[PDB]
Image 1: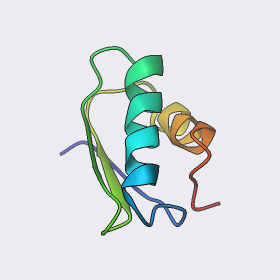
Image 2: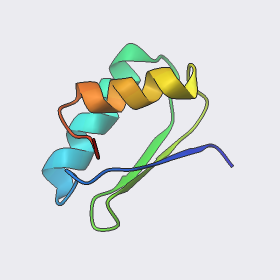
Image 3: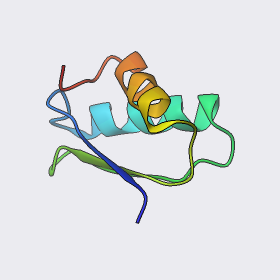
Image 4: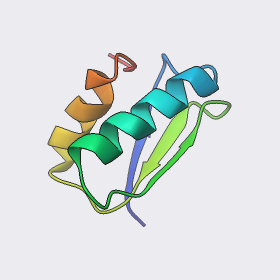
Amino acid sequence: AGLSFHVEDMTCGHCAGVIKGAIEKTVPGAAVHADPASRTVVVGGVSDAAHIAEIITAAGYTPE
């Protein structure tokens, strides 16, 4: 029961992979389960949900 973010830009594994890398890089010990077919990212223990949303956006893939 962690955080959930739905991303429009996610349409293939080339989006999920980058987001997962961005999260893990900027947040140590972060668990990321991403599904680009469902266009949805499941995020474990991370910094402020607002921050990690920006981190996901920082990957260039965002629903915004």
